[PDB]
Image (cartoon, rainbow over all chains, first blue to last red; front, side, top):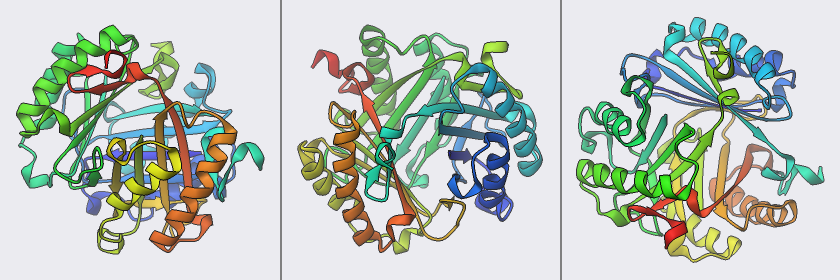
Length: 117
Length: 117
Length: 117
């Protein structure tokens, strides 16, 4: 899975090790191994969420197979909100998630694509 | 709507309050309330646009319903170019926009997805 | 084409001129002119790739027509991995690519969309 987190928290207010703890959280929530989880955190951005510049975070989750229905994404959403509200000390009104299904022909790995691996 | 702006302008050359003025602009252009507009600005990046590293900006716009046809996106494009060329003091050759339709099962909000709200 | 590169290398460890050399590389690999290539590099991020925070890079490639099959993307992947492993001095285990097809109604250029140009 690919997780990308944009936040207007400065880098020195993002907890040390967040990118590693998010790998372990995503592994349990999405049912994929932690060594196949990829996390990108982009702090110190200028953001408005719901029209407000108070601290906030945007998470994008992309994966093959597991983020492609409302019923699956409702479950994933509940668990990611619990994790992030605690780690970032944000209210649930200050986080949004987007889910993007991927197919194997879209993922370039070790000089080929996943269709052939 | 979700608006993401990448620019090679340094943070101290991006006008103060741009993320808030872009909420109000997007509200009028896309016909959605300003309190449902989300803006992310990422300044100080290394960019080439049309092969050139002169100051430039990339805007991504994602929304349910309203960015899914050529005729709608032509109108949105004209209005966003007018707003951004003035705010950033860039020529129209230095801006590109990408439009991405979303569906309600893709948006995680308050621990669920929008399909159920 | 649109190329977006996220890396946990600090800005002062990314080779000067990478955004320009990536325009020339993408032109040859994707068969589009260098003056239609757009590159965004975001350095200094907090990243884990395959569960590890060692130096790594994520590349996203979006284009009309040329990134929409496994056979095309296998070729593109091989060439981009050769370019990036040398430029960033990373192993092939530390890079992933995502490919995204676009349609002309999604691209805002000079105040319209590409459908009308």
